[PDB]
Image (cartoon, helix red, strand yellow):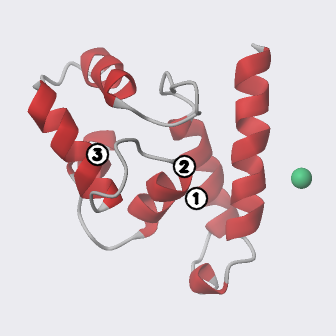
């Protein structure tokens, strides 16, 4: 409970940083999209760092009824992180959701 409430205020701080980021100065409905992405990201069982790891993905694909193998999950993450981290951070998740590049995880969400 306390873990999740402090998780979301950490995500809220990040959203507030995006609301002021000149990169997204274009985006229409930005406050709304960011709220929705925070709620979606909060649906994962995040790791000790508050990030989506192999475990978080596994649990999510299973809740959603979508079969993924070890390697497919590995690839779903490196695809979204461009291969520089083995976990998806909220920043990476938001940039994924806003970005025009397609991603298996982005397409799995919807
Ligand atoms: Zn604050």
**Mark 2, residues whose alpha carbon is within 10 Å: few (<14), some, or many (≥20)?**
many
On screen, residue 4 versus residue 55, left or right, reads right
- Label 2: which secondary element: helix
- Label 1: which secondary element: helix
Label of residue 33 in the image: 1
Residue ID for mark 3: 77
Q: CA distance from mark 1 to mark 2?
A: 13 Å
Q: CA distance from mark 1 to mark 3?
A: 22 Å
**1 and 3 marks in contact (CB < 8 Å):** no
- Label 3: which secondary element: helix
Front label number (1 vs 2): 2
| Quarter where residue 88 is shown | top left
Label of residue 42 in the image: none
Q: Residue at x 46, y 52 (%)?
A: 93
Location of residue 43 in the rendering, given as x and y in whole percent from the top left corner? 51, 27
| Quarter where residue 28 is shown | bottom right
**In front: 87, or 35?**
87
Q: Residue at x 32, y 74 (%)?
A: 100
| Quarter where residue 70 is shown | top left
Mark 2 near ligand 1 (CB under 8 Å)? no
Location of residue 17 in the rendering, given as x and y in whole percent from the top left corner? 74, 66
On screen, residue 53 versus residue 50, left or right, reads left
On screen, residue 95 versus residue 30, left or right, reads left
**Mark 3, residues whose alpha carbon is within 10 Å: few (<14), some, or many (≥20)?**
many
Front label number (1 vs 3): 3
Residue ID for mark 2: 90
Q: Earlier in the sequence, mark 1 or mark 2?
A: 1
Q: CA distance from mark 2 to mark 3?
A: 12 Å
**Mark 1, residues whose alpha carbon is within 10 Å: few (<14), some, or many (≥20)?**
some
């Amino acid at each position: 409970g306390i873990l999740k409430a402090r998780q979301e205020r950490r995500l809220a701080e990040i959203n507030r940083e995006f609301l002021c980021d000149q990169k997204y100065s274009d985006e229409e409905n930005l406050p709304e999209k960011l709220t929705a992405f925070k709620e979606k990201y909060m649906e994962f069982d995040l790791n000790n760092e508050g990030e989506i790891d192999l475990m978080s993905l596994k649990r999510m694909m299973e809740k959603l009824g979508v079969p993924k193998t070890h390697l497919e999950m590995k690839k779903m993450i490196s695809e979204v992180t461009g291969g520089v981290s083995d976990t998806i951070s909220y920043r990476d998740f938001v940039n994924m959701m806003l970005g025009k590049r397609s991603a298996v995880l982005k397409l799995v969400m919807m």
